[PDB]
Each structure stands twice: as C-alpha cells, then as structure tokens.
Length: 393
Ligand SMILES: [Br-]
Ligand SMILES: [Cl-]
Ligand SMILES: [Cl-]
Ligand SMILES: [Cl-]
Ligand SMILES: [Cl-]
Ligand SMILES: [Cl-]
Ligand SMILES: [K+]
Ligand SMILES: [Zn+2]
Image (cartoon, rainbow, N blue to C red; front, side, top):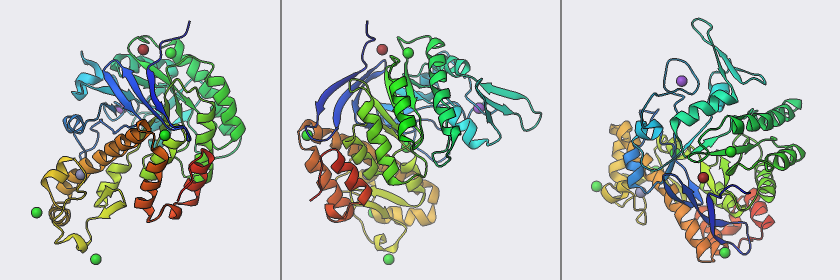
C-alpha cells in the first residue's frame, strides 16, 4: 500500500551516513549526491541551459517568479510547460515561490490563508495559498515541486518559529490534497523548526507521517552558527527515512557539501558558484583562485588542469585575468561555467568514492587539499564528521 519510491540506494558508506543513489524522475535518471544549479535565466549574467546540458547537468532549478507584472509565481501559458519554456530536456525542481515573496518584497504578510502582497502602485492584493502554489506547479509540469512553507529567519527566536513550523505541517497537507499529477510530479515536504531541536523533532515526526516522495531540510541557509548548522542537519537526517531523498536547501560551499554528504544528504542548491564568479574568483580543490590578482598575469595554465569544463579547455588564467579588467562581463560568464562544473565534478567525485568504499579517505584528501592538512579543518566540520565516524589525519 506504499507509494512507489523514486530513489534507489546504490551504496552506503559503512562508517558515515554518506549515500550514493539514483533519482528516477519523469525526465531521466539523476545520480546522487547531486548539486542542482539554477537553470532559470532571470539573470543577464549566467549560464544557458544548453551549456548546463553540455556540463552533464541532469537536474536544475527552475521558477517563474521573475516573470509577469506582479511578484509571486506566474503562469506561463505554454503548451510544453516550464520544460518547453526553458528548452530543458532534463529534470526540473521548482520552488513554491513563497520564499521569494516574503524575502524580496518585505511588504508581504504571512497568514494561515497564505502569502499576501499589496501592489505598490495600486494596492491590488496577490494571495499565494497552498492551493494556488500547487495549481501553478501542476501547470508548469516540473519533475519535483516543493511544498509551500511558512519560512522564518533562523536568527529570529520565539513563538513565531513554532507558529511557522505547525503552519508548514498544515500547509503540507493542503498541498497534498490540491496536488493533481502525482504520477508526473513529486511533492517534497520541507522540515522546519529553526534551530530548536524539539521543534524540528516534532516537525520530523509529524511530516514523515505523510507519504510524500521526498523530504527537504529547510531554514538552515541563514546566518546561524556552524555548530547549530551541522547539528540540525544531523538531527534531520537521523529521523528522515533512508529510502527517500534528503534535500538540504541553500548549501553550496565545497566543505559544507562534503560534510553534509557524510551526514546523509542527497540534494543541494546554492547560488554560491555564481556569486563567487562575480568577485573574479574560480573554484579549485584548494578553495578559490582570485584571478584579478597579478600573480596570474603571466600564468598561462588553465584554472585547473584536472577540470573538464570548456573554460579550462580553451582559456588560460592569464586570458581571464586580462578579461576581468577589460571585459568584466565576459569573464564572469567563463568563471560561471567553470564554478558550476567544479560543483558537478565535486559531487561526481564524492559519489565515486562512496561507490568504491573510500569515502572516509576521500574526505581526508579533500580537507588536506582545502586547508593544507586535514587537521587544519574548521572545528565545526571536525565535530560534524566525527559525529558520524570520520576522523581527520
Ligand atoms: Br512517481
Ligand atoms: Cl548555481
Ligand atoms: Cl503527494
Ligand atoms: Cl600579487
Ligand atoms: Cl593564452
Ligand atoms: Cl565507504
Ligand atoms: K512574478
Ligand atoms: Zn574549468
């Protein structure tokens, strides 16, 4: 009487909680752990979906909030849905549109009925209810659709956190009932609770009672402490079902990815690679190369001789160093292609080490290259790794 499972576990680390798996979605199989870039082209500065396809990306994020006349998710009235609008043959994960509404507008109010917004020019009100959030996602046809949740700042403390956690449970059940096409789209729940161990445990116990295809860990991209960050992640994965995906939203730093894979997470997203490129910085196994600095002026090697991305096939560090100072826009595009490929290659290398039963050794190699010697790893990541049985040498 159980719903079909979209995830297949290929290998599990004998020490940590690391998992190598496959997502079987309507638009093809996705290898996990997977970083998911933003396929939405709401930015002049970015990477096209055709280039994401060339990099091997088989699932990306896509949303329509940036379209239309008013803020909030928008219907596109396209025959082929958001896949046709994006020209994307692969998998799409679509947000609810609620986080962007309460975060960017800042004039929105959250009630039990949904997210409300009074127009700036005339005061016309747009209400984003769980019914309306799912009806839009059904029309977009995305492969994975996210629950509309009551998002609170992780730093904000008080009954508001508990209020949002219970409201997210009530909204989750509203999204389930309103969700047509469960044969084509997978609705994920979002675990709330902020930094409170008892609130998240209540949300974990309650939300896992629903038979949604996947579960997401929300409310942790905020500026909390790294100790509270990894503890809430480990708490979540310790009580989420192992036979279903775990989506940790908003984490993109290389060290945060390796640790949270070791904590049992399967899916990630973050605009960190794009923002890193705009500082003239390229992601490497040792951190990031600040290519604007003149040490690369006559450095004609690629960013990374091991990287397979087109930027490292065609352009050198010197060309990018000069391009950052003569055409900053074109250089941002080349670094964006690389930084996104580094994320893809990092996740692919993590998965290979889990399949080959050498994930703990992979983490030591990663920390040594990232921080000099694995013992120089940040204290918070040492605590998180040791809590699942990975010590650094
Ligand atoms: Br399914
Ligand atoms: Cl990205
Ligand atoms: Cl469902
Ligand atoms: Cl210098
Ligand atoms: Cl050159
Ligand atoms: Cl292993
Ligand atoms: K909009
Ligand atoms: Zn590259």
